[PDB]
Image (cartoon, rainbow, N blue to C red; front, side, top):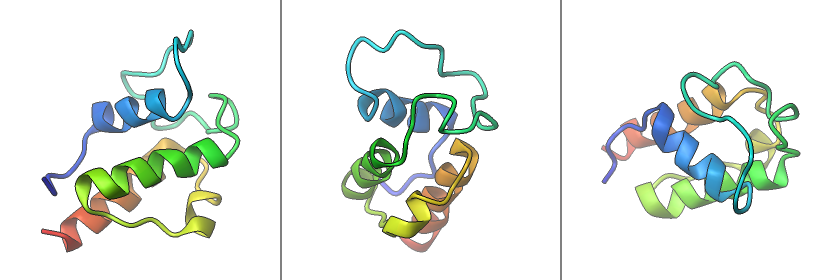
Amino acid sequence: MATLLTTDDLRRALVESAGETDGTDLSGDFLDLRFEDIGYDSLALMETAARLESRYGVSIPDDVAGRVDTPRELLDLINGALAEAA
């Protein structure tokens, strides 16, 4: 569905894009945590966006994904696209 995503939707993707058995703490309100701090270089960050693209019907440009600092922004990229996909 093109139903606007929440913190947890983003979380789910951020687990999947990270790897497997991710010993970290990424939930609640991680929106202000910079990708660099949470083990996100940018390729895995694109991985997040790309997965959300196919799943929710959005599309996220490459240079944008490798530009956003915080998950807040990435979530908003998705939600902005979802609003257009509604």
